[PDB]
Length: 55
Length: 165
Image (cartoon, rainbow over all chains, first blue to last red; front, side, top):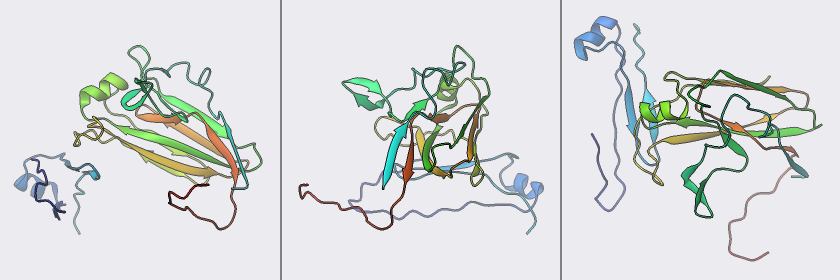
């Protein structure tokens, strides 16, 4: 999904990355064992790898 | 800076027999109309349909600090990754006595900037006299070509102005 800033000013965007406790909780929520998240803009680029462990 | 001399830390003609040192050009860095690239870096690309494991070292023998710069290339797609390096799962490693870091490319489509959906990160380090710096990669590495042996001063800054010198 993409968004283009057309509001004539800066847009503050917030988001989250979820790190489950166990592989079972991972599969209960997303069904995929080895996942990634990517966020990218013209000045931002970052890839997120979840860290599954019991805190 | 009290002393600043450029030298070819990794000569273009002889350093990379098993890799291509001439195809690493891009429309994002044009010169005289043609596609070009940075002068002090070489964008190594697979030779034939092969990118063998890369390993090159330099020992600072210049009697002073050496400024070394390099790049990591993050392609937009897996196809662009295979077009340039032929290897799907690659790494880059840079190591010295005070520097050690492993780089994993992040393949994804970023918004176009200068007609490029990929990205390239630029890094630098100061190699102390007598030290060794090692570059090791299976792809995505923009190897240094020119380094700079230098001696830093103390103070001064950067003036941003249209006032003439």
